[PDB]
Length: 101
Length: 101
Image 1 (cartoon, each protein chain N blue to C red):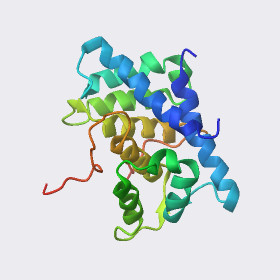
Image 2: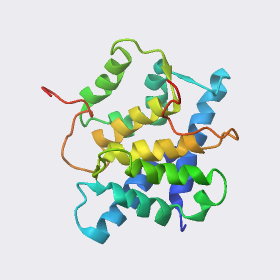
Image 3: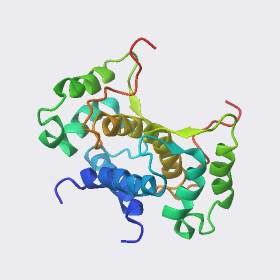
Image 4: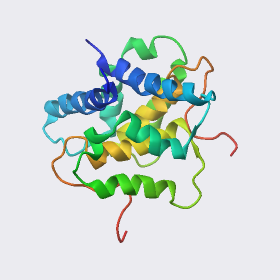
């Protein structure tokens, strides 16, 4: 357990590989899968009840402007947005997008 | 083990919290810590020998233009860049920055 970050990196990649098993293409993910992959890997334990609108914001992000593919980075940007949305801080911080700025 | 991604998210946040213990401010991380935090949490097991220049690129990123603070997202952008740099693909893919594009 000297370097658990390595497996956690593996957890993000290993879990991601499992979803690619449903379709077959592991070189890319569809933003719609962000909705299904988000709840399938994080159902109530995330959208339990705190900041329910945030789930809709992630869903509304798929409806942002021109959403179509998920690169390894886009899935992480969404996961990172999910972490800041609620990683451990008790303060309800919205997405990384500014309000008036 | 139904949802290991939750702990892995905790692994990134828990390990990150441990480094904040060295200084004291957990609301931000210094890009220099990216160099020390990168090797301290991922020493040889990463810069083992494959794509050694990549470590210098991460280090050169701190020397990019105006580097000073690491937001939760910047640390993840660097971690995401590290994952794509070598998450599981055997192809040596550089950073997420394009070459001529």
